[PDB]
Structure formats: structure tokens, C-alpha cells
Image (cartoon, rainbow, N blue to C red; front, side, top):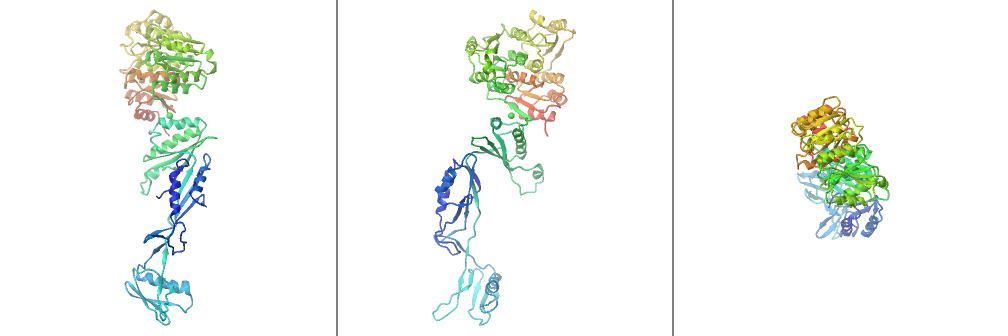
Length: 595
Ligand SMILES: [Cl-]
């Protein structure tokens, strides 16, 4: 057992019996100065000699939150010779000249002057003769490989009276001081990847961000991160892992320390940069707002948009109601309400819980709008909601989507100068204009093959824009729009596919934006995956920022517009999960987001 580490007080059982056993090792025979039965391990607690394992145990238990102590164990040098642990080792002369060297020390370093002075002569490569300088008697021949002798210990055995010399057993030097730090705290040893993938924090990564906002100060320790130059100059003799300790603390609370490392030095340097931002409270360059489902992602957008009790209303749509939802963006932005989601036959607890949080104590003066028919949100969920006590659960709906959009449209203030027209089958093209519309009170009118009379009545006199190709919004509807348009002109934003449409909306409206949001485009798992995009559009509207729609890599058309329009973006916010890291990297690269 040989190493210096840290354990928590709670999991220190193993160290304590480790010490109990080591305290039993004693010297059975000593020749270099120790005492028989002396312990062979020198063990201390904050440099105080350990009386027994139970005092270790009591010191560890008396540690309050955050406090730590160190145990030092050091072998004083021992070995087993013939079944007995000893403090000594037998050393032998290794060359002829070692022998004469010893004689020289005894003569000058010990004796001095002359009387007991000895003399040695090398006689061959591995024998030296030793005798006295005066009488030249008491002659011995030492060979290389013979045990060291003490010339101060003459063996005058009185069987008459003769000479002789005794041996020098030597000390086994102390080995090395190992330290175990014991902390009353929660400790973790994890790879850096578990917390951060290269550009985004992971869900485990955001738990730390959440603890800081919860009064935990973030502090760093044992920082052993190498600069690109220490990695550039492959001078050898360098570690294969970067590391550091993250410490979270709060008053009356038990701290927590998380040790991270990786074979990826850039990952670690990068992660340490994001955590400095989290500790400094400085807005990150890449933030993910998401949960394990469309319902928990919708709550995370709501937490970003509203502090407790700050929402004036609730917009509730069916979980799969993409058209009612994307059309609901200027409505959620206008009524300062989150777009939350319901099952048709129930309200998940996560959403009910976010309703309470954002309406707060004055819910009595606020409203809950349910968009869509009972085919999206049943009559029964509507009555469970009437049990709350909000000013009013008002349903905004019609016989179909076309009709529902005009109803949403009517809940907006008529003081708007812009309106958008999209097809009942164009949700993947349409979603691209939700933030812009939410950002300007512009309704989003959804139409079938021919424009309804009420639709024409709401847009007659205002400036209109079409989003979708002629197969979504017929060229006939277009002709009727140019007719009711103010300047007798209606532009159409329409790419070959939904990523080209998203690129045209971004090219047209977002020059100068200081943020970019990104969400799945519906190409993995179908159009229902556009729900993330629709819960975030009022959020992107509040930031005057666009939503890039992508699941895998950007199209070239998107890559080019981002490069022209979003050079001022100083933040990339990802909504939801399942977006390739490469598209986020591509986006970061084009807008020059880093360093
Ligand atoms: Cl994040």
C-alpha cells in the first residue's frame, strides 16, 4: 500500500483498520539503534504521534463540515531476517578500495594522532590486508563481498589473549512519508467528459451550475492544467492527464469536492474556462436549455423566461400541436406567458408544477389560454385547471388549425403592421418565422388552398409576408394577398427545403443579432420534434435573436447566412437534446464565438 490520497470521513473505515494493523508491526530484533518492540511505522495525525486506532477514529469523527486532517505513515525501514522483523541490513564491501576507505575514517575521523592507528594494503583486485602501523600485527584479509566491520570493536578473546574485529550491521533508512487526507465532505472522482463534451456542459455538468445559483460558491483547487505550450513542446516527462478540483460550499452545508481529469488537455482547459465563467457569474458562450422530454425542456425555457411569479399568463398547447404552437409565439410574447405543453388526457406534474411557479400568489388576476381543440387538450384537463382559481381558463380554438390561427390572431392587439402567411402543411418552414413574429406582434395566419374571408378581413390594409413555397401557400392565395396588401406587394421567403427556408429568414431579418438560438429541425423523428423550437421562439423574440433549425450538420445555405449575419452573436443557446456537436461547432466557428 503506497500512495497519497483523500477519503471522506464517512468512507474512512478501511484507512482506520489499515492503520490498526500497521500499528501492530514492531521490531523483534534491533541493531541499528531502534528498541525492540518499537513500532516500525511512524504514524501521525496533524503531526501528532497516534496513541492507537481509536484516537484516529475519534479525530476523524470530531471533524465538522469542511474540516480535514492528515494522517502520515512512514516506514522507518524494516525487513524480515529469519522470521523476525528487524531494523537492520547487512552491508558488504563492494570493491578493494571501499575497505581502505573505511580504515581511513577510523584512523582520522575517529582516532586522531597515533596509538591505535591501523594500516591497509591492497593485495589483489578483491583482497586488502589490515594490521597495525606500529606492531604490524593482528593481520586480517578482507575480501570484496565480506560484511562491513567496526574497527573500534576488537575481539580480544581471553583464551590466552588474541585479536579479531566485530561487524557493522547498518540501518535500513526510513522510506517515504505517505499522506492521507481525511475530509468531512462529499467527494467525486470523474472524467472531464462526464461534465462537458468539448463545447457544451452535460446534464451532470449543469447540476453544478444549478448548485452555484443555489448559494454555493464555486472555488478551484489542485489545478494541474498544462498550457498548449507544455503540450506543444513534446519534451517528454509530462503527465497524460489534466486535472483540477471543483469545490462547492455554503453556510451550514457540507461542502462537496469534484476531481476531474482527462487525456484531453484542451477539454479540461476549456471546461475550466466555462467553470470560471460559472464561478464569476459570467454568462456562458454555449448554454443548453433542455430536459429528458419536450415537457421538461418546455419548463427549462420557462425558467429562462420567468423568475417566480413573474408570468402574467399561461399558453397551453397539445404536446404534438406544432401548428397551434408555432402560431402561439406572438401570443406567448404578448401576454408574457410560457408555452407549456399538455397531454390530451392529462397534465404531467412537471408542467402543473411550472404553472404554479410562474403565476405565483396573484394567480387570481391571471389567465390560462388552452390553444387547440379537445383533440389536443381535452375538456377534462380544462376542468382540472378550473379548480386552480385563476382569473380565467379561456380556450382559443376553432374547427381546425386554419380556424385556430385566426382565433389566436384575434387575441393579439390589432395595432400590428405585419402579418405572416403559411400553409397548413408548412410547419417546418413556418417555425423559422415564429421568433420574428413573436418579436413584433405579427400574427401567423395558417391557410388552406384558398384564403378564408375572415383571414382577408384581418390582413386587409396591413403588410404581409409569405413563408413556404407555392405547394404550401398557393400562388392563388398570394394573388389575393397582394390585393389586400398595403403597398400592393408581398414577398415570399421559400427555400427548396426547411433548412434553406430557415437560412432565408435568418438572412432577411437578423443582421446584427447578438445571440443565436438552435433547435431540432424535425428531420430526426419527424415534425413533432419542432416542439422545442416552438416553446423557445418567445424566448428568442425577447432576445431579438433567430432560431437556427438543425439536427445534424448545417446546410451550406445556413452556414453562409450565419457567416454574414451573426458575426455579432456573443452567445449560442441550444434548446433540447439530440443536436449534433458538430452543428454547434460549425455555428460557433462561423460567428467567431470563441476567445
Ligand atoms: Cl449549459
